[PDB]
Image 1: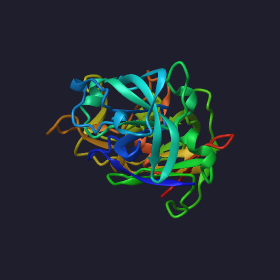
Image 2 (image 1 turned 90 degrees about the horizontal axis):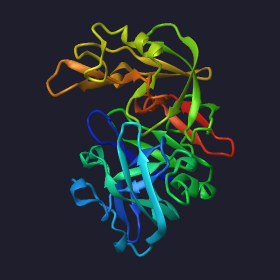
Image 3 (image 1 turned 60 degrees about the vertical axis):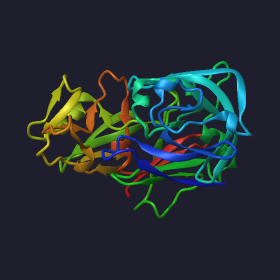
Image 4 (image 1 turned 135 degrees about the vertical axis):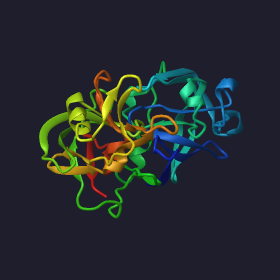
Length: 330
């Protein structure tokens, strides 16, 4: 089997991407944030505290003939941005782009933090990291991909995120028309439960490539590119007037600037992030200070190849017995 679904930016900045997901019988379609940095499929639901719902579409298990309470199971998750959610668990039929999993754990939120409530466009998350990170207790649950894997034509999924445009998540096949040149594969460590890999270096604009190992995670659920302070300083030094602002929470730059590109290495291959992808616009409405899309990972504890990086590539998440990651230009 295979599946193919379009993923759409939630706003004009590509802050996140939503993908329609069919849950239950008859189908309830919710727009979920596919997150290769976590491993829970959770949804706004008929159980979510009413004051914490503001415009989201909810899953109502009582209206699904295939829903079953997973008795005694609870979940609770905290994300890198400080947001969180928790609740109980149903199993139900879940389909993505024509690919169906029966008996998928659907984590029903009883509580969500303010960031989720305030984002009316995201009805929940669909985790695509390794199932070892799944938070369901006392019986850990598998991700949608892990459940689907044995049925897939090939044990892979691909992320093809757009810049200010829709893109695609495919399951079970590699669309050879969706990228240019060849795909370069690189080793993955699953030791922390992430799609963790080591970039071979970077360049700023038209500058020379610096060969240096940068361990980080491929994370579709993180907006920006978070890299070591040395690398980030080297980038922003090439933008007149750019500075790190503790009051704003990162690097800002004059909105009048033209940003240089940023290149990262994948083995001997190179992925170029155009300068425009690094512009996250005014820090507040009408400001002439703009927020940067490359930020320091210092104090996160891990480097994160988030959407800024991933959307510059066609990315293969190879879930074979020995997982790997592939990157191609597009």
